[PDB]
Amino acid sequence: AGILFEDIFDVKDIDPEGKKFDRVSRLHCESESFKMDLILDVNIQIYPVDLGDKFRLVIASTLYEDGTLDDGEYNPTDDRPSRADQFEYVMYGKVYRIEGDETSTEAATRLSAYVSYGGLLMRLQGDANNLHGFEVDSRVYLLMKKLA
Amino acid sequence: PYANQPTVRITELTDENVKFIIENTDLAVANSIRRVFIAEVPIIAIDWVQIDANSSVLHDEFIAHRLGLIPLTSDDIVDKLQYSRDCTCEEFCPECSVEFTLDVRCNEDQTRHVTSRDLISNSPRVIPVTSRNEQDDILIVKLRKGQELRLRAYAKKGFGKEHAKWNPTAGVAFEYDPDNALRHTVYPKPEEWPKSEYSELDEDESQAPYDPNGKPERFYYNVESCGSLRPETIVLSALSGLKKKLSDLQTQLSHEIQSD
Amino acid sequence: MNAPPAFESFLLFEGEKKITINKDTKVPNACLFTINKEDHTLGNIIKSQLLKDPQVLFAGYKVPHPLEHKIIIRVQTTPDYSPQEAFTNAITDLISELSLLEERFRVAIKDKQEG
Amino acid sequence: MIIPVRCFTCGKIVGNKWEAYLGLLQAEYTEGDALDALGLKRYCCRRMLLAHVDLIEKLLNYAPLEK
Ligand SMILES: [Zn+2]
Ligand SMILES: [Zn+2]
Image (cartoon, rainbow over all chains, first blue to last red; front, side, top):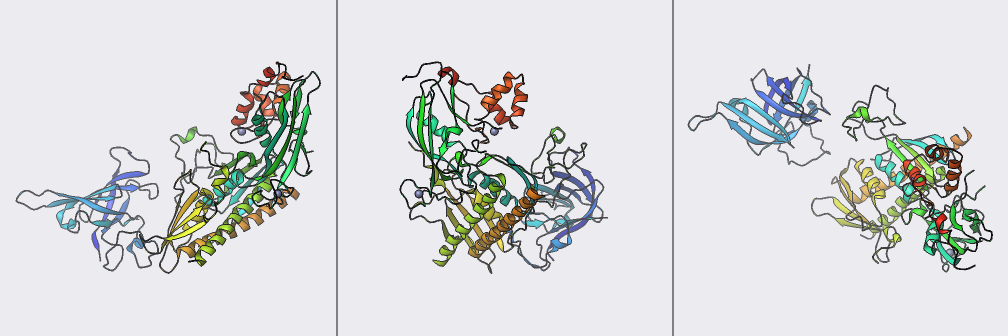
């Protein structure tokens, strides 16, 4: 499939530290199916997000519905079935950090994957079970859709 | 993959300016039209002076520069005349230039205003705008009793890209998105900014709600004419010249694809 | 002393041509059009019209130096298309646009003067 | 020394407006109202008439070189 992570999040807070940028807003969200915290920077100018909103988030390694790697190059004249069709807000970034509560002897029970979508930062942290798909320096997509 | 179908709506037409709106075109086309208004609409202007006598208090280059900036009526003649580059004659001929004479002498005590009315042309169609049959005549020089200015000018075809004296416009107001819906400007304090004359907003509202899917359409123009051409003639010449540049570029492009 | 004549910006020198086409070996199906004695007036419209073509993958232009009087237009198209063909179609579309705009402006003047 | 022909900024002709401007000023217009009467909208052309110093009038106080 090419999907590293999928879950349904609920916007719990927007810009707790205050509005830092005009067209970008930081959402602090928490899901229900996996109990994962999310910090996410979103362009609220084109995709406004209100407090209490509920959305489906899908971290994916590729947009093509069939397992097929991406070249990282912009190809607008691409006609294959892309899963971005199923979603409203799509971002493309790279994982730049994976933290965890591991010790010198114990493995990590909770992981924290950090992604950068061209400077819009995301932190998806929770059980390490759900963040096996993330390596550092690996390109991923956001695939976020609002639902009622 | 194909051309726009722009529409036009002229909201004001006087002898002094034309205020119009082009709608359903790209911002690049609108700005290129604006630029051609200023820089690639040919007119006639004095570009050659011979001072036979100048006892005035302004030196010869001052008089010459001042004559070059006098607008000359260029309406029907500019399309007919050739550039002296293209003319197969000597320095001058009636097919590429227009003769002017000026010959003034202050005899009385009391100051003689050498104005554009003293520029006498050989061509009745190309005359100083102020001299055309209100607004006074452009002042070339003031002469004291005993002072004298006699000169012979030639006016030629050119556009504002070579010298601002061949610029037919006296200001090209250009606007789009009067209510800042595309947010191409970002007002720190939108309430402090006055409304555009083309704004369509109630006074409580400072700018339109942001349009994520918009682009610039409906460009507003106010082309003011210096006098050489009519404003509608400026706009029609601009469209012809821009087009016709594109045609020349196409011809050279075809040759260059051919030759490969 | 060092002032170029004002005609240099728009007149062409002998033996130097208006437009030159050069592959871009960077990527496939890309070309550089070096156009002499033109400026932003044509570069901007050609670039925007090219951006209207869905078979154009890249369309950009630059004036490499304001004191020099040439523009570079880089056009990359899809493999089934050609940058030369894209450039030709962009110029044709701009010409048709300007012809239509001219005719409609004539009509709008016509109406304004008589009512 | 003499009124410029064109506005430096836009290129509007101001060389035929100096004499009318002075005539309006002696007619007890304010400078702004006089500039409004001559059709100088833009503060560039208003700058051209409002900031002009007619030095030629002083240069004409000297007798010419030839009688
Ligand atoms: Zn000739
Ligand atoms: Zn002005």
